[PDB]
Image: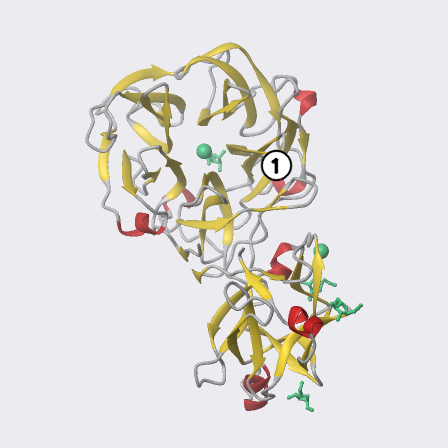
Protein backbone atom coordinates (compact mmCIF):
# COMPACT_ATOMS: atom_id res chain seq x y z
CA UNK A 1 0.00 0.00 0.00
CA UNK A 2 3.06 2.29 0.31
CA UNK A 3 5.11 3.53 -2.66
CA UNK A 4 8.79 4.12 -3.22
CA UNK A 5 9.43 7.50 -4.80
CA UNK A 6 10.49 8.51 -7.32
CA UNK A 7 8.60 6.18 -9.65
CA UNK A 8 10.52 7.25 -12.78
CA UNK A 9 13.52 9.53 -13.31
CA UNK A 10 13.48 12.02 -16.21
CA UNK A 11 9.73 11.61 -16.87
CA UNK A 12 7.50 14.67 -16.71
CA UNK A 13 3.73 15.23 -17.04
CA UNK A 14 2.98 11.66 -15.97
CA UNK A 15 -0.28 9.96 -16.85
CA UNK A 16 -1.35 6.60 -15.45
CA UNK A 17 -4.48 4.78 -16.61
CA UNK A 18 -5.73 1.63 -14.89
CA UNK A 19 -7.43 -0.65 -17.43
CA UNK A 20 -9.81 -3.58 -16.95
CA UNK A 21 -7.17 -6.01 -18.28
CA UNK A 22 -5.55 -5.76 -14.81
CA UNK A 23 -2.68 -3.54 -16.01
CA UNK A 24 -1.66 0.07 -15.31
CA UNK A 25 -0.50 2.05 -18.34
CA UNK A 26 2.03 4.80 -17.89
CA UNK A 27 2.93 7.53 -20.36
CA UNK A 28 4.88 10.76 -19.81
CA UNK A 29 6.81 13.61 -21.44
CA UNK A 30 10.43 12.61 -22.26
CA UNK A 31 13.25 15.18 -22.03
CA UNK A 32 13.87 15.12 -25.82
CA UNK A 33 10.19 16.00 -26.51
CA UNK A 34 10.39 13.81 -29.58
CA UNK A 35 8.18 10.76 -28.99
CA UNK A 36 5.41 9.12 -26.99
CA UNK A 37 6.52 6.28 -24.71
CA UNK A 38 4.37 3.70 -22.93
CA UNK A 39 4.85 1.06 -20.21
CA UNK A 40 2.60 -1.32 -18.29
CA UNK A 41 2.58 -3.38 -15.09
CA UNK A 42 0.03 -5.14 -12.87
CA UNK A 43 0.95 -2.90 -9.93
CA UNK A 44 1.88 0.75 -9.47
CA UNK A 45 5.31 -0.20 -8.07
CA UNK A 46 5.83 -2.60 -10.99
CA UNK A 47 5.86 0.45 -13.26
CA UNK A 48 9.25 1.57 -11.90
CA UNK A 49 11.00 -1.29 -13.71
CA UNK A 50 8.67 -1.93 -16.67
CA UNK A 51 10.33 -1.44 -20.08
CA UNK A 52 9.23 1.49 -22.30
CA UNK A 53 7.96 0.99 -25.85
CA UNK A 54 8.06 3.97 -28.19
CA UNK A 55 4.54 3.95 -29.63
CA UNK A 56 4.84 7.05 -31.83
CA UNK A 57 7.56 9.43 -32.97
CA UNK A 58 7.40 13.02 -34.23
CA UNK A 59 7.05 13.82 -37.94
CA UNK A 60 10.12 14.87 -39.93
CA UNK A 61 8.21 17.85 -41.39
CA UNK A 62 5.16 20.04 -40.70
CA UNK A 63 2.70 19.49 -37.83
CA UNK A 64 3.29 16.89 -35.07
CA UNK A 65 7.05 17.49 -35.63
CA UNK A 66 8.18 19.44 -32.55
CA UNK A 67 7.67 19.70 -28.79
CA UNK A 68 5.85 16.37 -28.28
CA UNK A 69 4.30 17.23 -24.87
CA UNK A 70 2.22 15.61 -22.09
CA UNK A 71 0.58 12.48 -23.54
CA UNK A 72 -2.45 10.90 -21.85
CA UNK A 73 -3.73 7.40 -22.60
CA UNK A 74 -7.42 6.51 -22.25
CA UNK A 75 -9.60 3.54 -23.16
CA UNK A 76 -12.86 4.74 -24.69
CA UNK A 77 -15.60 2.68 -26.38
CA UNK A 78 -13.39 -0.37 -26.92
CA UNK A 79 -10.43 1.63 -28.34
CA UNK A 80 -7.27 3.31 -27.04
CA UNK A 81 -6.83 7.08 -27.40
CA UNK A 82 -3.69 9.10 -26.78
CA UNK A 83 -4.00 12.89 -26.27
CA UNK A 84 -0.83 14.97 -26.69
CA UNK A 85 0.44 18.34 -27.85
CA UNK A 86 2.89 19.21 -30.63
CA UNK A 87 4.22 22.12 -32.65
CA UNK A 88 5.42 22.03 -36.26
CA UNK A 89 8.99 21.93 -37.68
CA UNK A 90 8.40 25.46 -39.10
CA UNK A 91 6.66 26.99 -36.03
CA UNK A 92 7.78 25.16 -32.87
CA UNK A 93 5.58 27.44 -30.74
CA UNK A 94 2.35 26.79 -32.67
CA UNK A 95 1.46 24.06 -30.19
CA UNK A 96 -1.87 22.33 -30.83
CA UNK A 97 -3.66 19.23 -29.46
CA UNK A 98 -3.61 15.91 -31.32
CA UNK A 99 -5.11 12.40 -30.86
CA UNK A 100 -3.93 8.85 -31.71
CA UNK A 101 -6.21 5.85 -31.86
CA UNK A 102 -5.54 2.12 -31.68
CA UNK A 103 -8.01 -0.77 -31.76
CA UNK A 104 -5.45 -3.29 -30.39
CA UNK A 105 -6.06 -5.19 -27.14
CA UNK A 106 -2.54 -4.32 -26.00
CA UNK A 107 -1.61 -0.69 -26.80
CA UNK A 108 2.12 -1.36 -26.36
CA UNK A 109 2.28 -3.59 -29.42
CA UNK A 110 -0.63 -2.20 -31.48
CA UNK A 111 -0.42 0.21 -34.39
CA UNK A 112 -1.65 3.77 -34.10
CA UNK A 113 -3.90 5.89 -36.35
CA UNK A 114 -3.53 9.71 -36.21
CA UNK A 115 -7.01 11.23 -35.75
CA UNK A 116 -5.64 14.74 -36.32
CA UNK A 117 -5.86 18.04 -34.48
CA UNK A 118 -8.59 18.67 -31.94
CA UNK A 119 -10.16 21.71 -33.58
CA UNK A 120 -11.15 24.68 -31.42
CA UNK A 121 -12.84 28.01 -32.41
CA UNK A 122 -9.66 29.97 -31.55
CA UNK A 123 -6.38 29.29 -33.32
CA UNK A 124 -3.93 29.72 -30.47
CA UNK A 125 -1.43 27.91 -28.23
CA UNK A 126 -3.25 24.81 -26.91
CA UNK A 127 -2.12 21.77 -24.95
CA UNK A 128 -2.73 19.40 -22.02
CA UNK A 129 -5.98 17.82 -23.28
CA UNK A 130 -7.62 15.53 -20.74
CA UNK A 131 -10.90 13.64 -21.06
CA UNK A 132 -13.29 12.49 -18.34
CA UNK A 133 -16.90 11.44 -17.89
CA UNK A 134 -19.45 13.06 -15.57
CA UNK A 135 -22.92 11.40 -15.35
CA UNK A 136 -22.21 9.39 -18.52
CA UNK A 137 -21.35 12.57 -20.47
CA UNK A 138 -17.78 12.83 -21.82
CA UNK A 139 -15.97 16.18 -21.56
CA UNK A 140 -12.63 17.55 -22.70
CA UNK A 141 -10.64 19.98 -20.58
CA UNK A 142 -7.46 21.67 -21.80
CA UNK A 143 -5.16 24.69 -21.51
CA UNK A 144 -5.31 27.37 -24.21
CA UNK A 145 -4.42 31.00 -24.81
CA UNK A 146 -7.34 33.40 -24.75
CA UNK A 147 -5.73 36.02 -27.05
CA UNK A 148 -7.74 38.86 -25.47
CA UNK A 149 -6.06 38.09 -22.12
CA UNK A 150 -2.56 39.15 -21.08
CA UNK A 151 -1.32 35.69 -20.01
CA UNK A 152 -0.02 32.32 -21.29
CA UNK A 153 -2.97 29.88 -20.92
CA UNK A 154 -6.39 29.64 -19.31
CA UNK A 155 -8.53 26.54 -18.68
CA UNK A 156 -11.24 25.43 -21.11
CA UNK A 157 -13.92 22.74 -21.02
CA UNK A 158 -16.25 21.35 -23.70
CA UNK A 159 -18.49 18.42 -24.45
CA UNK A 160 -17.22 15.90 -26.96
CA UNK A 161 -18.79 14.52 -30.13
CA UNK A 162 -16.20 11.73 -30.24
CA UNK A 163 -12.83 11.20 -28.60
CA UNK A 164 -11.07 13.59 -31.06
CA UNK A 165 -13.80 16.20 -31.65
CA UNK A 166 -15.48 18.72 -29.34
CA UNK A 167 -19.20 19.43 -29.50
CA UNK A 168 -20.64 22.93 -29.18
CA UNK A 169 -18.44 25.74 -27.90
CA UNK A 170 -15.73 25.80 -25.18
CA UNK A 171 -16.15 27.58 -21.85
CA UNK A 172 -13.18 29.26 -20.21
CA UNK A 173 -13.44 28.19 -16.58
CA UNK A 174 -10.26 29.60 -14.98
CA UNK A 175 -7.65 32.21 -15.81
CA UNK A 176 -4.37 32.81 -13.95
CA UNK A 177 -4.92 35.94 -11.85
CA UNK A 178 -3.86 35.03 -8.28
CA UNK A 179 -0.27 35.81 -7.19
CA UNK A 180 0.79 32.16 -6.94
CA UNK A 181 -0.61 31.55 -10.45
CA UNK A 182 1.45 34.36 -11.99
CA UNK A 183 5.09 33.80 -10.93
CA UNK A 184 7.33 33.84 -14.01
CA UNK A 185 4.37 33.33 -16.36
CA UNK A 186 0.63 33.72 -15.98
CA UNK A 187 -0.26 30.03 -16.44
CA UNK A 188 -3.17 27.63 -15.88
CA UNK A 189 -2.25 24.30 -17.51
CA UNK A 190 -2.39 20.49 -16.99
CA UNK A 191 -6.10 20.11 -16.03
CA UNK A 192 -6.90 16.87 -14.20
CA UNK A 193 -10.22 15.62 -12.90
CA UNK A 194 -11.14 13.52 -9.88
CA UNK A 195 -14.71 12.82 -8.77
CA UNK A 196 -15.85 12.15 -5.24
CA UNK A 197 -19.03 12.43 -3.16
CA UNK A 198 -21.05 14.11 -5.91
CA UNK A 199 -18.38 16.73 -6.63
CA UNK A 200 -16.01 17.27 -9.56
CA UNK A 201 -12.51 18.46 -8.63
CA UNK A 202 -10.33 19.78 -11.42
CA UNK A 203 -6.76 20.34 -10.41
CA UNK A 204 -4.44 22.28 -12.66
CA UNK A 205 -0.87 23.54 -12.64
CA UNK A 206 0.11 27.17 -12.22
CA UNK A 207 3.12 29.54 -12.61
CA UNK A 208 6.40 28.78 -14.40
CA UNK A 209 7.59 25.17 -14.47
CA UNK A 210 10.28 26.09 -11.91
CA UNK A 211 10.16 25.81 -8.09
CA UNK A 212 7.09 28.03 -8.32
CA UNK A 213 5.04 25.32 -10.10
CA UNK A 214 2.09 24.25 -8.01
CA UNK A 215 -1.45 22.90 -8.16
CA UNK A 216 -4.59 24.96 -7.85
CA UNK A 217 -8.09 23.48 -7.98
CA UNK A 218 -11.57 24.15 -9.27
CA UNK A 219 -14.63 22.55 -7.63
CA UNK A 220 -18.13 21.92 -8.97
CA UNK A 221 -21.15 19.78 -8.19
CA UNK A 222 -21.57 16.78 -10.52
CA UNK A 223 -25.21 17.81 -10.96
CA UNK A 224 -24.39 21.35 -12.17
CA UNK A 225 -23.85 22.55 -15.75
CA UNK A 226 -20.09 22.06 -16.17
CA UNK A 227 -20.14 24.39 -19.17
CA UNK A 228 -21.35 27.29 -17.04
CA UNK A 229 -18.24 29.03 -15.64
CA UNK A 230 -20.33 29.93 -12.57
CA UNK A 231 -20.57 26.24 -11.57
CA UNK A 232 -16.81 26.27 -10.78
CA UNK A 233 -15.20 27.76 -7.67
CA UNK A 234 -11.42 28.28 -7.60
CA UNK A 235 -9.41 27.57 -4.43
CA UNK A 236 -7.73 30.81 -3.32
CA UNK A 237 -4.50 29.08 -2.24
CA UNK A 238 -2.50 26.31 -3.96
CA UNK A 239 -3.65 22.81 -3.06
CA UNK A 240 -0.15 21.37 -3.62
CA UNK A 241 3.14 23.22 -3.63
CA UNK A 242 6.88 23.13 -3.06
CA UNK A 243 8.04 21.70 0.29
CA UNK A 244 11.58 22.77 1.15
CA UNK A 245 11.53 20.56 4.27
CA UNK A 246 11.01 17.46 2.17
CA UNK A 247 13.24 18.79 -0.67
CA UNK A 248 10.43 18.65 -3.26
CA UNK A 249 10.21 21.55 -5.64
CA UNK A 250 7.61 22.66 -8.20
CA UNK A 251 5.22 19.71 -7.94
CA UNK A 252 2.66 19.70 -10.71
CA UNK A 253 1.14 18.49 -13.95
CA UNK A 254 -0.75 15.75 -12.13
CA UNK A 255 -3.13 12.96 -12.98
CA UNK A 256 -5.17 10.59 -10.87
CA UNK A 257 -5.33 6.85 -10.66
CA UNK A 258 -6.51 4.22 -8.12
CA UNK A 259 -4.82 1.69 -5.84
CA UNK A 260 -4.53 -2.05 -6.55
CA UNK A 261 -7.69 -2.78 -4.52
CA UNK A 262 -9.53 0.11 -6.22
CA UNK A 263 -10.11 1.60 -2.74
CA UNK A 264 -7.69 4.55 -2.72
CA UNK A 265 -7.22 7.47 -5.07
CA UNK A 266 -3.61 8.07 -6.11
CA UNK A 267 -2.09 11.48 -6.99
CA UNK A 268 0.42 11.11 -9.85
CA UNK A 269 2.75 14.10 -10.44
CA UNK A 270 6.23 15.41 -11.23
CA UNK A 271 8.70 17.56 -9.34
CA UNK A 272 12.44 18.23 -8.87
CA UNK A 273 14.66 17.56 -5.86
CA UNK A 274 16.32 21.00 -6.16
CA UNK A 275 15.15 24.60 -6.27
CA UNK A 276 17.06 26.53 -8.96
CA UNK A 277 17.03 25.52 -12.61
CA UNK A 278 20.36 25.47 -14.40
CA UNK A 279 20.31 26.51 -18.07
CA UNK A 280 17.33 26.98 -20.40
CA UNK A 281 14.33 25.95 -18.20
CA UNK A 282 12.83 23.99 -21.11
CA UNK A 283 16.06 21.93 -21.46
CA UNK A 284 16.30 20.81 -17.83
CA UNK A 285 15.47 17.07 -18.00
CA UNK A 286 15.39 16.29 -14.28
CA UNK A 287 11.68 16.31 -13.45
CA UNK A 288 10.64 12.96 -12.04
CA UNK A 289 7.35 11.06 -11.63
CA UNK A 290 6.03 10.49 -8.08
CA UNK A 291 2.98 8.87 -6.45
CA UNK A 292 1.15 9.49 -3.19
CA UNK A 293 -2.28 8.54 -1.83
CA UNK A 294 -5.07 11.13 -1.86
CA UNK A 295 -6.91 11.55 1.44
CA UNK A 296 -10.45 12.78 1.63
CA UNK A 297 -11.44 15.49 4.08
CA UNK A 298 -14.69 15.13 6.09
CA UNK A 299 -16.28 17.91 3.99
CA UNK A 300 -15.68 15.75 0.87
CA UNK A 301 -12.77 17.75 -0.61
CA UNK A 302 -9.46 16.07 -1.47
CA UNK A 303 -6.39 16.63 0.73
CA UNK A 304 -3.10 16.23 -1.12
CA UNK A 305 -0.96 17.27 1.84
CA UNK A 306 2.62 18.06 0.81
CA UNK A 307 4.98 16.37 -1.61
CA UNK A 308 6.51 13.69 0.59
CA UNK A 309 10.20 12.92 1.15
CA UNK A 310 11.85 10.50 -1.27
CA UNK A 311 11.90 6.82 -0.45
CA UNK A 312 8.96 5.04 1.18
CA UNK A 313 5.71 6.98 1.64
CA UNK A 314 4.51 7.88 5.12
CA UNK A 315 1.44 6.40 6.86
CA UNK A 316 -1.34 7.60 9.14
CA UNK A 317 -2.28 6.02 12.48
CA UNK A 318 -5.87 5.99 13.72
CA UNK A 319 -7.14 5.23 17.23
CA UNK A 320 -8.83 1.91 18.06
CA UNK A 321 -11.52 3.47 20.22
CA UNK A 322 -11.81 6.72 18.22
CA UNK A 323 -11.43 5.40 14.66
CA UNK A 324 -11.86 8.90 13.16
CA UNK A 325 -8.99 10.35 15.24
CA UNK A 326 -5.43 10.26 13.98
CA UNK A 327 -2.07 10.78 15.67
CA UNK A 328 -0.94 14.28 14.72
CA UNK A 329 1.29 17.07 16.04
CA UNK A 330 0.29 20.63 16.88
CA UNK A 331 2.79 23.14 18.26
CA UNK A 332 4.96 19.97 18.19
CA UNK A 333 2.82 18.29 20.87
CA UNK A 334 1.41 14.90 19.81
CA UNK A 335 -2.32 14.20 20.17
CA UNK A 336 -5.14 12.35 18.47
CA UNK A 337 -7.67 14.41 16.53
CA UNK A 338 -10.31 13.94 13.87
CA UNK A 339 -10.57 15.89 10.59
CA UNK A 340 -6.96 16.97 10.35
CA UNK A 341 -6.85 19.76 7.76
CA UNK A 342 -3.06 20.08 7.81
CA UNK A 343 -2.72 16.50 6.63
CA UNK A 344 1.07 16.16 6.96
CA UNK A 345 0.79 16.74 10.73
CA UNK A 346 -0.74 13.19 10.81
CA UNK A 347 1.73 11.42 8.49
CA UNK A 348 4.72 9.51 9.83
CA UNK A 349 7.10 7.15 8.28
CA UNK A 350 8.15 4.00 10.06
CA UNK A 351 11.91 3.70 10.09
CA UNK A 352 14.41 1.37 11.78
CA UNK A 353 14.61 2.44 15.43
CA UNK A 354 17.09 5.13 16.37
CA UNK A 355 18.22 3.00 19.35
CA UNK A 356 18.68 -0.29 17.44
CA UNK A 357 17.88 -3.76 18.82
CA UNK A 358 15.03 -4.22 16.29
CA UNK A 359 13.07 -1.18 17.47
CA UNK A 360 11.19 1.30 15.26
CA UNK A 361 11.00 5.09 15.13
CA UNK A 362 8.31 7.34 13.66
CA UNK A 363 9.68 10.15 11.49
CA UNK A 364 7.51 13.21 10.73
CA UNK A 365 6.47 13.63 7.09
CA UNK A 366 6.47 17.46 7.21
CA UNK A 367 9.49 17.70 9.55
CA UNK A 368 11.98 15.13 8.32
CA UNK A 369 14.63 14.47 10.97
CA UNK A 370 11.95 15.06 13.59
CA UNK A 371 10.46 12.06 15.40
CA UNK A 372 7.75 11.15 17.86
CA UNK A 373 9.59 11.17 21.19
CA UNK A 374 8.55 11.20 24.83
CA UNK A 375 9.80 13.48 27.59
CA UNK A 376 8.41 13.36 31.12
CA UNK A 377 5.99 10.75 29.70
CA UNK A 378 4.49 13.32 27.26
CA UNK A 379 4.84 12.74 23.51
CA UNK A 380 6.22 15.43 21.16
CA UNK A 381 7.61 15.68 17.61
CA UNK A 382 11.16 16.94 18.03
CA UNK A 383 14.36 17.15 15.99
CA UNK A 384 16.92 14.42 16.47
CA UNK A 385 19.94 16.17 18.00
CA UNK A 386 22.11 13.03 17.73
CA UNK A 387 22.13 12.43 21.49
CA UNK A 388 21.70 8.99 23.04
CA UNK A 389 18.89 10.38 25.19
CA UNK A 390 16.88 11.45 22.10
CA UNK A 391 17.46 8.16 20.34
CA UNK A 392 16.21 6.23 23.39
CA UNK A 393 13.21 8.58 23.74
CA UNK A 394 12.29 8.07 20.03
CA UNK A 395 12.52 4.29 19.80
CA UNK A 396 9.68 1.86 20.35
CA UNK A 397 9.11 -1.87 20.06
CA UNK A 398 6.25 -2.70 17.74
CA UNK A 399 3.74 -4.98 19.45
CA UNK A 400 0.52 -6.63 18.35
CA UNK A 401 -2.44 -4.36 19.17
CA UNK A 402 -3.50 -4.57 22.80
CA UNK A 403 -7.20 -4.47 21.90
CA UNK A 404 -6.67 -6.06 18.45
CA UNK A 405 -3.77 -8.54 18.25
CA UNK A 406 -4.68 -9.37 14.63
CA UNK A 407 -4.93 -5.95 12.95
CA UNK A 408 -3.98 -3.42 15.65
CA UNK A 409 -0.55 -2.00 16.51
CA UNK A 410 0.82 -0.98 19.91
CA UNK A 411 4.10 0.85 20.60
CA UNK A 412 6.09 -0.09 23.70
CA UNK A 413 8.69 2.41 24.89
CA UNK A 414 12.25 1.08 24.42
CA UNK A 415 13.73 2.84 27.50
CA UNK A 416 10.57 2.53 29.61
CA UNK A 417 9.44 -1.10 29.06
CA UNK A 418 5.85 -1.66 30.21
CA UNK A 419 4.93 1.88 29.11
CA UNK A 420 3.00 2.22 25.86
CA UNK A 421 2.11 5.08 23.56
CA UNK A 422 -1.48 5.90 24.52
CA UNK A 423 -3.89 8.78 24.22
CA UNK A 424 -5.40 10.35 27.31
CA UNK A 425 -7.58 13.48 27.07
CA UNK A 426 -6.51 13.26 23.41
CA UNK A 427 -2.86 14.07 24.21
CA UNK A 428 -0.32 11.32 23.57
CA UNK A 429 1.69 9.92 26.47
CA UNK A 430 3.66 6.85 27.41
CA UNK A 431 1.90 5.05 30.24
CA UNK A 432 1.44 1.58 31.74
CA UNK A 433 -1.61 -0.38 30.54
CA UNK A 434 -3.69 -2.30 33.07
CA UNK A 435 -7.39 -1.72 32.28
CA UNK A 436 -9.53 -2.49 29.20
CA UNK A 437 -9.70 1.24 28.39
CA UNK A 438 -5.88 1.54 28.69
CA UNK A 439 -5.56 -1.27 26.15
CA UNK A 440 -7.90 0.55 23.74
CA UNK A 441 -6.07 3.88 24.32
CA UNK A 442 -2.80 2.12 23.34
CA UNK A 443 -4.05 0.43 20.14
CA UNK A 444 -3.77 2.02 16.68
CA UNK A 445 -4.17 1.10 13.00
CA UNK A 446 -1.90 2.04 10.11
CA UNK A 447 -3.70 2.81 6.81
CA UNK A 448 -6.87 0.77 7.54
N1 LIG B 1 7.63 30.62 -22.69
N2 LIG B 1 6.74 30.00 -22.38
N3 LIG B 1 5.80 29.44 -22.09
C1 LIG B 1 6.12 28.38 -21.10
O1 LIG B 1 5.84 27.08 -21.66
C2 LIG B 1 4.43 26.81 -21.44
C3 LIG B 1 4.24 25.31 -21.21
O2 LIG B 1 4.68 24.94 -19.91
C4 LIG B 1 4.01 27.61 -20.19
O3 LIG B 1 2.91 28.45 -20.53
C5 LIG B 1 5.24 28.46 -19.84
O4 LIG B 1 5.93 27.89 -18.72
N1 LIG C 1 1.28 26.79 14.91
N2 LIG C 1 1.31 25.93 14.17
N3 LIG C 1 1.22 25.18 13.34
C1 LIG C 1 1.11 23.82 13.87
O1 LIG C 1 2.32 23.48 14.61
C2 LIG C 1 3.16 22.72 13.72
C3 LIG C 1 4.10 21.85 14.61
O2 LIG C 1 3.39 20.83 15.35
C4 LIG C 1 2.17 21.95 12.87
O3 LIG C 1 2.75 21.50 11.64
C5 LIG C 1 1.16 23.04 12.56
O4 LIG C 1 -0.12 22.46 12.27
N1 LIG D 1 11.66 10.58 33.90
N2 LIG D 1 12.33 11.15 33.19
N3 LIG D 1 13.01 11.66 32.43
C1 LIG D 1 12.27 12.10 31.22
O1 LIG D 1 11.01 11.40 31.09
C2 LIG D 1 11.35 10.13 30.48
C3 LIG D 1 10.04 9.48 29.98
O2 LIG D 1 9.36 10.36 29.07
C4 LIG D 1 12.29 10.53 29.36
O3 LIG D 1 13.21 9.47 29.05
C5 LIG D 1 13.04 11.72 29.95
O4 LIG D 1 12.89 12.78 29.03
N1 LIG E 1 -11.19 12.26 28.51
N2 LIG E 1 -10.91 11.22 28.87
N3 LIG E 1 -10.66 10.15 29.15
C1 LIG E 1 -9.45 9.75 28.43
O1 LIG E 1 -9.39 10.54 27.19
C2 LIG E 1 -9.90 9.71 26.15
C3 LIG E 1 -9.37 10.33 24.85
O2 LIG E 1 -7.95 10.60 24.97
C4 LIG E 1 -9.24 8.38 26.51
O3 LIG E 1 -9.86 7.28 25.84
C5 LIG E 1 -9.51 8.30 28.00
O4 LIG E 1 -8.45 7.58 28.64
CL1 LIG F 1 -5.75 20.69 11.36
NA1 LIG G 1 -2.79 16.06 -18.05
User: Residue 256: x, y in percent?
Assistant: 47, 39
**Label 1 Cα neighbours within 10 Å, binned few <14 / some 14-19 / many ≥20:** many
Q: Is residue 249 above or below residue 35?
A: below
**Any part of residue 384 in sight:** no
Which image quarter is the N terminus in? bottom left
Question: Which residue bears the numbered disc 1?
Answer: 217
Quadrant hosting residue 178: top right
Q: Nearer the viewer, residue 133 or 358?
A: 358
**Any part of residue 60 in sight:** yes
Quadrant hosting residue 75: top left
User: Residue 64: x, y in percent?
Assistant: 30, 23
Q: How many marks?
A: 1
Question: For this view, does 350 lie left or right of residue 74?
Answer: right
Residue most toward the top?
A: 168
User: Residue 156: x, y in percent?
Assistant: 55, 22
Q: Is residue 226 above or below residue 71?
A: above
Q: Nearer the viewer, residue 124 or 130?
A: 130
Amino acid sequence: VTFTNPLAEKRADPHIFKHTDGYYYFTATVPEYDRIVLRRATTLQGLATAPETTIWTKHASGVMGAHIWAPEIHFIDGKWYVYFAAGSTSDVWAIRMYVLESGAANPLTGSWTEKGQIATPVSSFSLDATTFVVNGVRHLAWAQRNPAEDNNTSLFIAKMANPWTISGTPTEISQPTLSWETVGYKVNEGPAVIQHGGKVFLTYSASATDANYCLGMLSASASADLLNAASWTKSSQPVFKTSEATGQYGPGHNSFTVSEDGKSDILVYHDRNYKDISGDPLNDPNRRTRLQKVYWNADGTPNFGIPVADGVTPVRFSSYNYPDRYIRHWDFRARIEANVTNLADSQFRVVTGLAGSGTISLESANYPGYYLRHKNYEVWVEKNDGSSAFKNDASFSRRAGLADSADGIAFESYNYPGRYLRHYENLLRIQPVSTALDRQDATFYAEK
